[PDB]
Length: 48
Length: 70
Image (cartoon, rainbow over all chains, first blue to last red; front, side):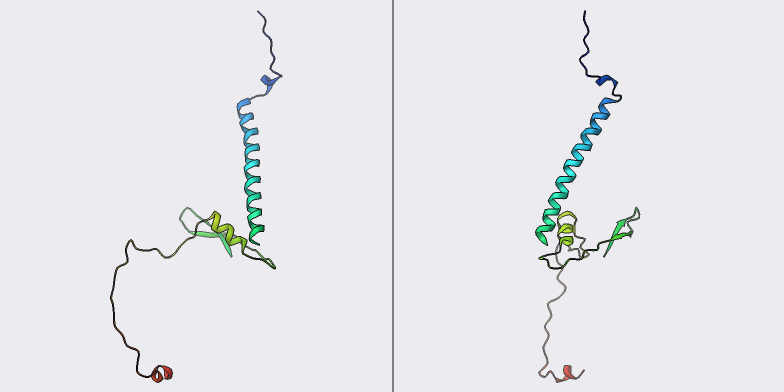
């Protein structure tokens, strides 16, 4: 039997799940903050 | 005006200020923001139903000179 590792070194990233959940939050948080801050800056400009 | 945080005892203490200053404008963006995002604290609280107290007759005087004088 042949065992081929086609895993791109992924196994050497410790605590992978937490690492992927952190990258996801850092991205979703940045998305949702930018959405909210841009919507409020538009509404402020609209009012003034 | 002051920005206040609610403490665990429900006392409020000052942690900063609102400080907005604009020239020519069509509106106050501070209050527009706080209306949309915050809730209004109303000191007045309506009863379930108004309680009639009285329907009272009174008269205005024949002359306004006494009130004018005092």
